[PDB]
Amino acid sequence: PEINIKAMNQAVNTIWLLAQRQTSGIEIINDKVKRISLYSREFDEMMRDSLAQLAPVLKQLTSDAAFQTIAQIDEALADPSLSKDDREALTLERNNLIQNLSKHIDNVIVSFTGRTSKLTNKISDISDMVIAERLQDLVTQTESQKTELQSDIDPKTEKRNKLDADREKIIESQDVIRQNNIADMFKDFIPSAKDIDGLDFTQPKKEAIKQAIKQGAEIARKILGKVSEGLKYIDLADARMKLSDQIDQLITETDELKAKIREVELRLSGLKDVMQIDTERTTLLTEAVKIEQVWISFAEQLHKLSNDEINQQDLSNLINGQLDFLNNLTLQYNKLK
């Protein structure tokens, strides 16, 4: 049964990473993620240690003293010139040694099962953990909010364009007024249509100037709400600057909405990270379950051999196969480093 420890350790590490770099503000999810990352790191360390620790326990069984001794007992029992008292004594020695070997194998199975059981309990601590209920709905809510924020932003850009166009018209009027120094001719109030129309330059020049000045004045009065008859230059300049400040108000609003979009997108990223955490957890848990099943089958077969007696060679093949397997896993672990 081939197992990929590389994927297991890489999933553990990615889980830790994503927990470290998760940006979603939910306190519950943050706490749960921290807990699961700690459980996974504890499990990685405990697995490394369990592999390094288990091989000696099984190794002790193969080099059991009682086996060569049993052989020597049988050798002695091969002698015909022996008393039935001594024969039964040696027979009891052999049978007792078989009983001690079985007892020792059971003690080994208990120790091995305990070591594996601690890992199993940690795997259970990991699996039982639930990050959040129906996360996909949370992601849906977050993306819906992001869409709503963008849809509320777009009209702000359109309105900024309209006010900027109005500012352009107003400042055109101001700069052209100074260009022709009209302020000096009509210093008290803006010249009416007839007043400017009566004198100077060309009818195209006159008409262009009139349209520009009237456009500026109309926009200014509309912004300030006063009627056209006010005809004051100061009203024009005041409206210009006041509309510009309103544009700055729009900039403030837009910056706030952009910051909220930043938070929402950051959150969505965090949630995606949590989903990837769950996926990597699944990846890890699959390999862990495979190793657990391997070890349980091994323990069952070893219990079967304990129930049966002697049969040293097949037992050695079993234990050595398991040791080679453990060494394979340890080698796989060491390779990644």
Image: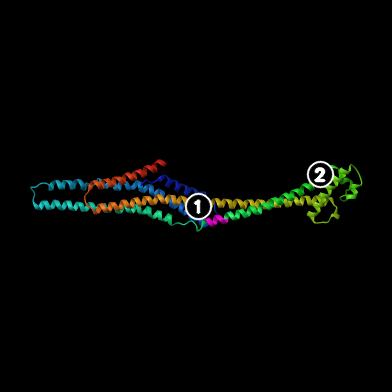
Q: Residue 143: horizontal and vertical position, in percent? A: 58, 54
Q: Residue at x 38, y 49 (%)?
A: 47
Q: Residue at x 77, y 47 (%)?
A: 168
Read off the residue under disc 1.
275
Q: Amino acid at mark 1?
A: Met
Query: Label 1's element?
Result: helix
Query: Label 2's element?
Result: helix
Q: Residue 163: horizontal and vertical position, in percent? A: 74, 50
| Residue 59 in view of the camera | no
Going by the image, does 304 lie left or right of 81? right
Q: Nearer the viewer, mark 2 or mark 1?
A: 1
Residue extending farthest to the bottom is: 133
Quadrant placement of the C terminus:
top left
Please provide the residue range marked out in magenta.
Answer: 136-141
| Residue 273 in view of the camera | yes
Q: Are marks 2 and 1 in contact (CB under 8 Å)?
A: no
Q: Residue 30: horizontal and vertical position, in percent? A: 51, 54
Which quadrant of the figure has residue 321?
top left
**For mark 1, does the 10 Å Cα neighbourhood hold few (<14), some (14 to 19), or many (20 or more) residues?**
some
What label does residue 175 carry, if any?
2
What predominant SS class does the magenta segment belong to? helix
Going by the image, does 14 lie left or right of 307? right
Going by the image, does 251 lie left or right of 337? right
Q: Observer-nearest residue: 145 or 174? A: 145
Q: Residue at x 40, y 41 (%)?
A: 335
Q: Observer-nearest residue: 163 or 238? A: 163
Q: Amino acid at mark 2?
A: Asp
